[PDB]
Amino acid sequence: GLTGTGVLTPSSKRFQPFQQFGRDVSDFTDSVRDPKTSEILDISPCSF
Amino acid sequence: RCTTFDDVQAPNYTQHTSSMRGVYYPDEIFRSDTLYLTQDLFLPFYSNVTGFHTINHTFGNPVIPFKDGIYFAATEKSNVVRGWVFGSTMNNKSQSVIIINNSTNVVIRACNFELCDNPFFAVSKPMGTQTHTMIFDNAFNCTFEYISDAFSLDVSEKSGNFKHLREFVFKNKDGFLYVYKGYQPIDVVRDLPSGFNTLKPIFKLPLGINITNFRAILTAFSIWGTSAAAYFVGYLKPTTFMLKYDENGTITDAVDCSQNPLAELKCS
Amino acid sequence: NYNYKYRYLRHGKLRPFERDISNVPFSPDGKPCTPPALNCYWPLNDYG
Image (cartoon, rainbow over all chains, first blue to last red; front, side, top):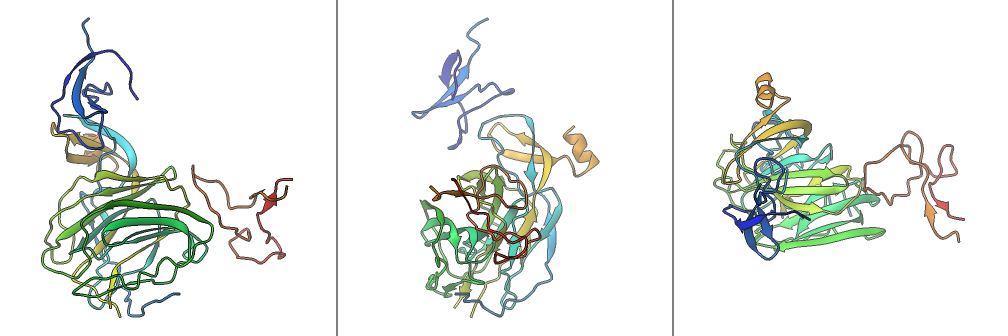
């Protein structure tokens, strides 16, 4: 249910079973659970 | 077949404090190191608790209407209080969902059921059998069934500490029913301890019927019988909370707005 | 085709996604009637 453009790396969570998203500072998702069991941070600022 | 017991005493509707209970996860999303605001039907801090102390003489099985859901809590030692009669009219005609167990697995079922005036589990003290689980009376204009996780679940009578603490939240929402689960080891004589426990977003349900009335379901030790136990009632209020998530993703503190000028200043 | 129906008598509005099968023999202050009593009808109405 997500789209976008970014730089991927694995997560560092205490991630939850019902859970997918991270929105870290506010509402910007910043960490995703892959649908095939991976925990991956999404640092979308590619470079700018 | 209203197989209704008679020694069901009227208590004085014992009153307690709703200090810090009812906090759950409003989102489905990790965050960290925030104060998050949201506006929702929550149990306020410090408010009333209509606690029901069913004892060896006093039995507490009333009918209560829905009224913005409930904060629910029950101190059972191997699980007396399975079952909720979330009904409409408490007769044969009722849009009723029933939340019960086959002692291993969770059986929830909504249909127009015959609601007896007191159907009871004829549960014995050393074993714990639903010998008289006669609740499935009628089936006309039926709607829905659901069977959840089969998991570890006991029946029979114990004592000691309030070994199982069921902290539940039952919340109607846009037709759905949202039901949460907690667990806590507590030891009070008969009453509520002081403490908070974050409730988990467990059960969300596609039901969609006008849920008016409810009853609670206990185990009548077959003539009834109860242990040294109690269960609580709390009502929700459309208030505003500021939560404090940690880096672990665990609720460590909650602050209401409509409680104290200091509390609203905290959420301000 | 008078087989399928609708209902047109109730105490008021509704919340979303919510349903009652209950054929209530309506009276405007509760009062469970048997039609043909006064202000006591049934809500069933065919499709024509």
